[PDB]
Image (spheres, coloured by chain):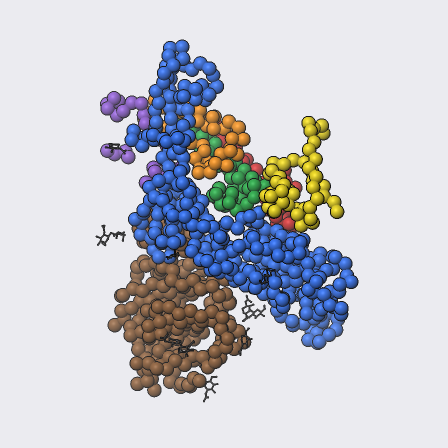
Chain colours: A blue, B green, C brown, D orange, E purple, F red, G yellow
């Protein structure tokens, strides 16, 4: 009862005459809704991961996956090890997040150089063949390739770069094979000292150790922007409710509030809206394309007017900023009172 | 403001990371907001004087 | 196949002043009755813009693509058609091409065997590229279309995309404010470091109508934008003038 | 001569956390800042009258 | 008369303004 | 004052270790110096009164 | 350090399921045979 809440706030068993601010009241949510895109196909994940004929480190292939459904549960079809590090996002069953645009890169590198595929690393591969940005968001997957990339004489189809003029900007591809002159002389010759051909093969032989074993690596680069989200995950939709408190998941955006019809002149390109406080205030349903206004559930402060406990025990309650009709009646439990 | 975290919204931090790592971001945001509100209170006290 | 013409009168490019033109919506968020601050690639206020005139007078030079391009056309009778973008403008490298049909737009990106002077000639001649190598991205859509028409275009190429913003107004340049609404977001990603325009010339040699087009280049700048009761920009202020 | 100043009240949880419950659970672990802030603001409010 | 949506935006973030004890009529 | 990071000099720390930790230490130094500025401003306000 | 009680949970699993016995891990053994809480404190020793 209000008197006991006043006692708990004051940390005393006896209260004097006055008015005390105890706590706040707010209407607790009822249902749950989820609206996600309507696409039903599946993303070309199986045309990059397996990829019988594969790519080299200095000409790494790039695939642009768009307008499909992403299921990251179907990845456990390979031998273990599956090193597997996601930066800026966790993979522990977080395939429930929509995404703007996804890049897939793939290359084979050596054993000890798998650690070089990470932000803030300096090394031969890091500054000569492939460099991630400092604030990169995405995932890196690595696995062994002895069973599929082994040959008796060693495969020369795999090469890497050791010498170049300077470092690489993030996500930059170099294919040039022009000679690299070092000391003073003009070179312009096929071979000779200071006249270097900037490519060296791996020569992978099964007789080598684990640290020399070929490793195949795939890198997924994600993007989060103010876009309709093309790619997404397998989350079922749900009929939307209006004029009624409801926690919602609109295309990856979680919130809680009363969703109503809005009459704000959204232009065709505009996706959502914001207010003075830099918060979401209007959203477009990505199945009916209707603008909806968001307004949180009623809330306010509660005060207890009481004479001294030595005088009586009955109290009065003041709800601050409420029009005496928005005072909730409650059904079983929908108030923090 | 982000105060050094990855975003200025709590739901996107909790829905995109594991509880092991979300705690750091949430702690840093909470500390920033508490400091801002403390500064507001101090300024109000001086003005009231 | 392309023809050779020897009816050109060379003339130095003209210059004129862009007052307050070249402000566009930079994000896909709706804001109302709010003064906001943005930091993006814009066209500085009160700047030189290069003036090209066609009427004999025939000008289709090559112009750089440093960071972005602002292209204005004051026109009637629909002379200017489309644009070509690329690095070397030959068969060795990819290049992007946009053309307007009679009632369509076609965009596609690949290597070309471009001529020296692509152009278009009731029209039934379209002499731009003599060979179509294999192309990756192709797209078709609705047409973009005394001087009365004023077309304003902003081309940006960052973050592996290609942003085209456009505006059309029924009227040098007019002194006033008019924002530009996003119209195309095509994600291809070449340099695009030089570009050349395409007009329509018809035989009488040949006769070309009076058309004037204006070229400017964008720079990173900070702007203050005003959103009125609706989501329409009414005024802007450059914090570096 | 000015005499009085505007009386303001601040809700901790709705400012810092908002519509997140786990944020509130973490916020329970950072002491009694909210009691101090609310008490100071109430003192200013009474002083105005 | 010489001394004079933002209020709603502030209120939705938990910042409210309380009324005075004495109205203007009483001071007058 | 190091404020708990490696070194007060930031040009050194920017050329010693990797960006992932250098950013964290720079953030810590920035927070400490901002705290110092707030303390100075509050003391100045009281002396001005 | 002196503790109240020690609980030894022993089982034999395949090599792929070794990582499944850990906080914040999802697997067949996790949701069907043996689940560890997030706030679990102790040690795990797996040997061939
Ligand atoms: C609009 O212009 C395009 C561009 O040339 C025309 O597309 C050509 O159509 C013919 C006949 O279908 C094809 O043989 C060519 O290969 C197309 N060109 C290219 C580059 O693919 C189109 O016909 C024009 N008219 C429309 C679309 O109605
Ligand atoms: C865009 O294409 C141009 C080729 O024209 C590339 O720029 C060249 O870079 C080399 C290496 O420094 C220079 O020697 C050339 O002089 C440059 N070209 C010109 C015309 O100056 C450029 O690398 C490409 N952009 C990329 C790959 O992002
Ligand atoms: C914002 O939008 C409203 C709604 O269209 C505009 O109000 C209309 O303006 C036109 C143009 O003068 C009038 O013909 C209508 O009668 C207006 N409608 C109403 C209901 O008043 C308003 O002008 C717009 N604000 C601008 C353009 O600044
Ligand atoms: C390669 O394609 C097959 C075809 O079904 C698929 O089963 C397999 O999972 C793909 N490879 C990988 C590594 O996913
Ligand atoms: C699927 O969603 C799209 C989104 O606009 C909608 O237009 C379409 O009617 C939906 N189809 C079904 C069968 O729900
Ligand atoms: C409160 O309710 C009364 C009766 O319906 C109404 O006249 C008045 O305008 C309401 N006030 C507010 C602030 O809603
Ligand atoms: C027309 O111009 C092209 C452009 O290089 C040239 O190759 C061709 O020889 C020219 N035609 C004649 C007849 O000179
Ligand atoms: C524009 O260019 C002319 C030269 O043609 C120069 O005199 C003038 O100062 C330039 N304007 C600005 C604003 O730089
Ligand atoms: C097809 O495109 C490639 C670009 O990867 C180019 O090398 C090749 O010459 C093109 N084919 C023809 C016939 O031009």
The residue under the point 53% across, 44% down is B5
Q: Tell me which image quadrant ligand 4 sits in.
A: bottom right
Which of these two is toward me, A18 or A104? A104
The residue under the point 30% across, 85% down is C204
**Residue C125 image-quadrant placement:** bottom left
Q: Position of residue D34 (x, y in %)?
A: 47, 28
Q: Position of residue F38 (x, y in %)?
A: 51, 35
Q: Is residue B47 visible?
A: no
Q: Position of residue C220 (x, y in %)?
A: 46, 57
- Given the current orientation, which residue lies at the most extreme top position? A310
- Given the current orientation, which residue lies at the most extreme right position? A207
The residue under the point 36% across, 18% down is A315
> Where the C terminus of chain A falls, by quadrant?
top left
**Residue A191 image-quadrant placement:** bottom right
Q: Position of residue B12 (x, y in %)?
A: 49, 45
Q: Is residue A13 above or below residue C222?
A: above
Q: Going by the image, does B37 lie left or right of A183?
A: left
Q: Going by the image, does C233 lie left or right of A167?
A: left
> Where the N terminus of chain A falls, by quadrant?
top left
Q: Is residue A224 above or below residue C184?
A: above
Q: Going by the image, does C107 lie left or right of G12?
A: left
Q: Is residue B24 visible?
A: yes
The residue under the point 30% across, 59% down is C176
Q: Is residue A89 above or below residue A22?
A: below
Task: Tell how many labels.
Answer: 0
């Amino acid at each position: 009862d209000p008197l006991s809440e006043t006692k708990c706030t004051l940390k005393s068993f006896t209260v004097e005459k006055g008015i005390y601010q105890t706590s706040n009241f707010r209407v607790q949510p009822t249902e749950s809704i989820v609206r996600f895109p309507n696409i039903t196909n599946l993303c070309p994940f199986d045309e990059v991961f397996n990829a019988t004929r594969f790519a080299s480190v200095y000409a790494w292939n790039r695939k642009r996956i768009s307008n499909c459904v992403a299921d990251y549960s179907v990845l456990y079809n390979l031998a273990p090890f599956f090193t597997f590090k996601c930066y800026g996002v966790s993979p522990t069953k977080l395939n429930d997040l929509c995404f703007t645009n996804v890049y897939a890169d793939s290359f084979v590198i050596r054993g000890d150089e798998v650690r070089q595929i990470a932000p803030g690393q300096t090394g031969n591969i890091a500054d000569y063949n492939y460099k991630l940005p400092d604030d990169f968001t995405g995932c890196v997957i690595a696995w062994n390739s002895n069973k599929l990339d082994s040959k008796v004489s060693g495969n020369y189809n795999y090469l890497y770069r050791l010498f170049r003029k300077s470092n690489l900007k993030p996500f930059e591809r170099d294919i040039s094979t022009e000679i690299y002159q070092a000391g003073n002389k003009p070179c312009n010759g096929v071979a000779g000292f200071n006249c270097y051909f900037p490519l060296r093969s791996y020569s992978f032989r099964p007789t080598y150790g684990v640290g020399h074993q070929p490793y195949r690596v795939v890198v997924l680069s994600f993007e989060l922007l103010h876009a309709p989200a093309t790619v997404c995950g397998p989350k079922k939709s749900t009929n939307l409710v209006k004029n009624k408190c409801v926690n919602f998941n609109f295309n990856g955006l979680k919130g809680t509030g009363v969703l109503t019809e809005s009459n704000k002149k959204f232009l065709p390109f505009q996706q959502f809206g914001r207010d003075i406080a830099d918060t979401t205030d209007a959203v477009r349903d990505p199945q009916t394309l209707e603008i909806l206004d968001i307004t949180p559930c009623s809330f306010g402060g509660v005060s207890v007017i009481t004479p001294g406990t030595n005088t009586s025990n009955q109290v009065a309650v003041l709800y601050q900023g409420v029009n005496c009709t928005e005072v909730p009646v409650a059904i079983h439990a929908d108030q923090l009172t | 403001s982000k105060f050094g975290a990855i975003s200025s919204v709590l739901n996107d931090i909790f829905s995109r990371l594991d509880p092991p790592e979300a705690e750091v971001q949430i702690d840093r945001l909470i500390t920033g907001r508490l400091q801002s509100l403390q500064t507001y209170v101090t300024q109000q006290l001086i003005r009231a004087a | 196949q392309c023809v050779n013409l020897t009816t050109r009168t060379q003339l130095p490019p003209a210059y004129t002043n862009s007052f307050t033109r070249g402000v566009y919506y930079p994000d896909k968020v709706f804001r109302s009755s709010v003064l906001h601050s943005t930091q993006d690639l814009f066209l500085p206020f009160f700047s030189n813009v290069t003036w090209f005139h066609v009427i004999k007078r025939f000008d289709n030079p090559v112009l750089p693509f440093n960071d972005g391009v602002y292209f204005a056309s004051i026109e009637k009778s629909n002379i200017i058609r489309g644009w070509i973008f690329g690095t070397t403008l030959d068969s060795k490298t990819q290049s992007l091409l946009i053309v307007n049909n009679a009632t369509n737009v076609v965009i596609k990106v690949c290597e070309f065997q471009f001529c020296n002077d692509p152009f278009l000639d009731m029209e039934s001649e379209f002499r731009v590229y003599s060979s179509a190598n294999n192309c990756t991205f192709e797209y078709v859509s609705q047409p973009f279309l005394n001087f009365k028409n004023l077309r304003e275009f902003v081309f940006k190429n960052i973050d592996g995309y290609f942003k085209i913003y456009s505006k059309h107004t029924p009227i040098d340049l007019p002194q006033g404010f008019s924002a530009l609404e996003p119209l195309v977001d095509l994600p291809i990603g070449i340099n695009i470091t030089r570009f050349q325009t395409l007009l329509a010339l018809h035989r009488s040699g040949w006769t070309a109508g009076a058309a004037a087009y204006y070229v400017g280049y964008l720079q990173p700048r900070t702007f203050l934008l005003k959103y009125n009761e609706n989501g329409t920009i009414t005024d802007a202020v450059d914090c570096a003038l | 001569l000015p005499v009085s100043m505007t009386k303001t009240s601040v809700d901790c949880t709705m400012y810092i956390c908002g519509d997140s419950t786990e944020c509130s659970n973490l916020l329970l672990q950072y002491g009694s800042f909210c009691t101090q802030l609310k008490r100071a603001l109430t003192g200013i409010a009474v002083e105005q009258d | 008369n010489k001394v004079t949506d933002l209020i709603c935006a502030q209120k939705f973030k938990g910042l409210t303004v309380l009324p005075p004890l004495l109205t203007d009529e009483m001071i007058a």
